[PDB]
Amino acid sequence: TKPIVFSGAQPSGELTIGNYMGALRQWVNMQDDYHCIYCIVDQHAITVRQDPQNLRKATLDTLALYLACGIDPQKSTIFVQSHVPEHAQLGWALNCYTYFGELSRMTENINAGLFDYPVLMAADILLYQTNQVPVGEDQKQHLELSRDVAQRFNAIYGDIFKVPEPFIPGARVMSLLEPKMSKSDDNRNNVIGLLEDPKSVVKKIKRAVTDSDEPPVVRYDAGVSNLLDILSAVTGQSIPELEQHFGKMYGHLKGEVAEAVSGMLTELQERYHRFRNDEAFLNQVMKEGAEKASAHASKTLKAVYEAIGFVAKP
Amino acid sequence: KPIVFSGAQPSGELTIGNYMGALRQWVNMQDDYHCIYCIVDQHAITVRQDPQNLRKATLDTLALYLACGIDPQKSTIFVQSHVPEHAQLGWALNCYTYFGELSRMTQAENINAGLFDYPVLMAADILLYQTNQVPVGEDQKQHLELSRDVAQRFNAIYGDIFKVPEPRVMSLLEPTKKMSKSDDNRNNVIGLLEDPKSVVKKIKRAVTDSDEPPVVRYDVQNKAGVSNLLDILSAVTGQSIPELEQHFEGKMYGHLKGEVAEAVSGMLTELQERYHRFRNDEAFLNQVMKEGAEKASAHASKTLKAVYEAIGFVAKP
Ligand SMILES: [Ca+2]
């Protein structure tokens, strides 16, 4: 049994080139070393009012994109959250072991889902005996609540849950017009999406901030440096060996980058469309993932219900 | 047939006031209504429980409702935790409930989130079954009204997915307050599973008045103690109260206490005979919980899948 890694994927989330070359490209190559779990959290998504048609479409978009990146439905467990009842069941039970004050510290006319979703996050992770969690900086507090709830529950009932640990990377990709590239960027021009057409990549790379050194030379030190990090990650080349290739101006660099990133995204995107348009295949993937997820999750939930004192479902 | 939903705490301490008033009445209407009795063990854990006692009290409650006459073939009786759709809809309805609506729910220390959020789960329990009517007490009126508001709010967004639900024994030593399981002095309370000799003793010590000479006459204002014993006697036996005023003309209070104790005791001995039979047959209780949970899930899943389709979730394949 390998270490279990759990990651949540927002249905509306837009994966950037930073998300891919930095983290997800490595995670794909390590699916034989870890039991990786990817949960498309549509129950977390409806804490914000959602257009139903866009929610359904975005869930399928996200599934197809992760499959396009190489997530293997048989090696890993990839599923839609609402297809696995155990998430809501454990979410309710852990409400009774979470303090109202803890949720208040997470930050009226908000809905109860926004207030309570940190408990559902804890259930998402603890269901699968998760060992490690890749947490963004924005999610640090949520992960520490999951640890505190797991320890509190185990102190009462015994070692039912594993106490999850945050996990660390690692290609560095910086925001183009402000050299870290983030999927949360309020400025779209700072990032390149995985579903970005070649023309828009060319336009964002050409417009990337750079330093007006005279004469313009290619050297790692913040604009020019970003393009060296991005190009090196795509081509697997050393930064200095790249500088050997560039006498050329910053326009040579920006052109070279844009061509490489678009070459890599094109291979990802054709896989994306082949999976995305095959709705029957996606239904099979969600069925396999949900059934595998529930089999694993029910082992933990039934031990939780046993310890709480519920009559076991006959 | 109209659908009626009632939640039963897994406590196993029904009082004779609860039975004669509420539960006994519903037992006779199982042919005219689709009655749903849900033993709400997920609500119970909003207060920390001893694990073994919770399990025992859930089976105690089931056996007790069975002995009172709830028929698992006419009605649907099940344990809440056996039907995952309750928690599933509970989470979804959180997103359509305002924080302030739960904050204004009066019914502390370091409260846990379940104690705050359980009114949402109550709404989920009711709405899963297209429920028409919920027989709540006065102290759960707010909870029912919140369930109605959430159903209306959801329907106003997505269309009519939910049905909107529709909008006397006293303490023996304190006959101006209704018989309460929470009473600190347990000699105020008669439970359905109270030993007959114990029930007769408490009835014998029930408060009365100081009329010289004693008079047995229904006047709640001046003779609360005697009027209470006449309501209990009228409830067990069905005799109209003026009949007992005529039967006790010239009789003393001790005669009436002997009459209430005997009648109450007889009712509790038939109920307890059935209870111990059901409760000692755990295989029978398991099969009732299995069947009840399958029926409950069959109806609940229809509503939950319609809710998920309106919200925009991908349908589970
Ligand atoms: Ca495979």
Image (spheres, coloured by chain):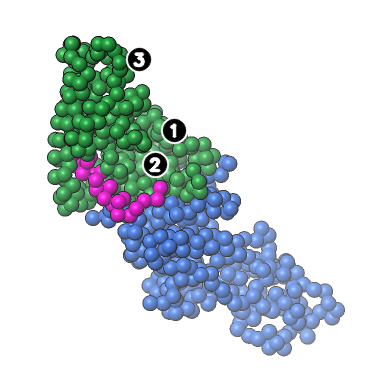
Chain colours: A blue, B green
Label 1: which residue?
B142
Neighbourhood count class around disc 3 (C-alpha, 10 Å): few under 14, some 14–19, many 20 upward: few
Q: Secondary structure at mark 1?
A: helix
Q: Number of marks in the image?
A: 3
Give the label on residue B191, or none: none
Q: Secondary structure at mark 3?
A: loop
Residue A270: x and y in percent read: 50, 70
Q: Are marks 2 and 1 in contact (CB under 8 Å)?
A: no
Q: What residue is drawn where x is 43% and y is 51%?
A: A96
In space, the residues marked 2 and 1 are separated at their CA atoms by 11 Å
Q: Secondary structure at mark 2?
A: helix
Q: Quadrant of the C terminus of chain A?
A: bottom left
Q: Foreground mark, 3 or 2? A: 3
Q: What chain does mark 2 sit on?
A: B
Q: Where does the magenta region start and end?
A: B47-68
Note whether residue B250 is visible. Answer: yes
Neighbourhood count class around disc 1 (C-alpha, 10 Å): few under 14, some 14–19, many 20 upward: some
Q: Which of pointers 3 and 2 lies earlier in the amino acid sequence?
A: 2
Mark 2, ligand 1, within 8 Å: the answer is no
Label 3: which residue?
B221
Q: Which of pointers 1 and 3 lies earlier in the amino acid sequence?
A: 1
Residue B278: x and y in percent read: 16, 45
Dot 3 amino acid type:
Gln
